Image (cartoon, rainbow, N blue to C red):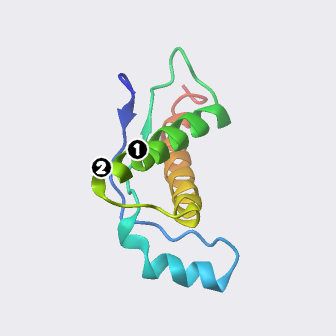
Amino acid sequence: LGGYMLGSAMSRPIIHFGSDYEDRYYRENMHRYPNQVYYRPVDEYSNQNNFVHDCVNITIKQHTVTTTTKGENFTETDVKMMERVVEQMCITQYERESQAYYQR
């Protein structure tokens, strides 16, 4: 990362994927997932969705790196759930400054 920023914590939001199985499974298994994300400031490199990818990947793969050192093995489904959580949290932390970027 070397020069990213980090956001505040939030208590793990629910992400209504579109099925009752997943909506439950999440609350059964929410206590494993990340609750913060990593992204740069907007001054040189600024983007919309590219910046969500370079947030989400860099956070997700930070877990999928650490998993090997944590003696964990996030399932492909766990990674898929984490992706969504990381997206909405990163988009949240985008809006807060994007409204202070496109309104300056």
- Find the residue positioned furthest to the right: 18
Q: How many discs appear?
A: 2
Q: CA distance from mark 1 to mark 2?
A: 8 Å
Q: Amino acid at mark 1?
A: Val
SS assignment at label 1: helix
| Labels 1 and 2 touching (C-beta < 8 A) | yes
Indicate the quadrant containing the N terminus: top left, top right, bottom left or bottom right: top left
Which residue bears the numbered disc 2? Answer: 69
Q: Amino acid at mark 2?
A: Thr
Q: Position of residue 36 (x, y in %)?
A: 38, 50
The foreground one among 23 and 89 is: 23
- Could you tell me which residue is drawn at 42 percent across and 72 percent down? 30
SS assignment at label 2: helix
Compared to 60, does 73 lie above or below? below
Crowdedness of circle 2 by 10 Å Cα count: few (<14), some, many (20+)? Answer: few
- Could you tell me which residue is drawn at 58 percent across and 66 percent down? 77
- Could you tell me which residue is drawn at 46 percent across and 61 percent down? 74
- Could you tell me which residue is drawn at 68 percent across and 80 percent down? 19
Q: Position of residue 82 (x, y in %)?
A: 51, 59
From the viewer's perspective, tell me whether residue 36 is left or right of residue 70.
right
Q: Say which quarter of the image contains residue 95.
A: top right
Which residue bears the numbered disc 1? Answer: 65
- Find the residue positioned furthest to the left: 70
